[PDB]
Length: 70
RNA sequence: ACUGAAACGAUUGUUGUGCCCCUGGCGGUCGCUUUCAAUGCCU
Image 1 (tube, rainbow, N blue to C red):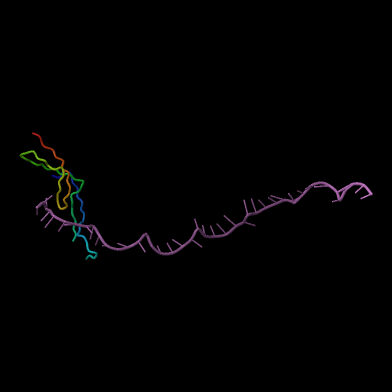
Image 2 (cartoon, rainbow, N blue to C red):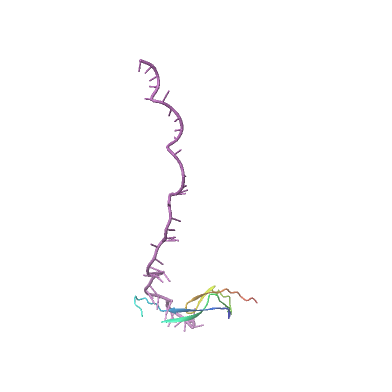
C-alpha cells in the first residue's frame, strides 16, 4: 500500500559506443521521497533483510520491520 | 524469469563580433643679492 509517494519522469537511452552514430524511452519512476507499507505472514521467526532491491533498475529499498505481538 | 534479464538524452558548438577614460586647462601670481665700507697707512 502506498503511504507517501511521488513520481519522476526521467528519459533513458542506448549508448553510442562507436565514434560514429546514426532507441530511447521515458520512465515514470517512483521517487526517493516515497514510503510503502506491506505485511508478511509466517509460521516461524524470519530473518528479513533490512535492504531489498526492486524493479527495472534493481533499486534500493530500506525495509524497517516490526513483529506484531499477540 | 522481481509489472524480470542488458539500458549514457548522446554527438558538435568561442558570450561572439566593434569600440581611445575621452574631451581643455600656463605651477600660476608678487619679489632689488639687498645693506655698510677711504686702496688705506708712512716716506
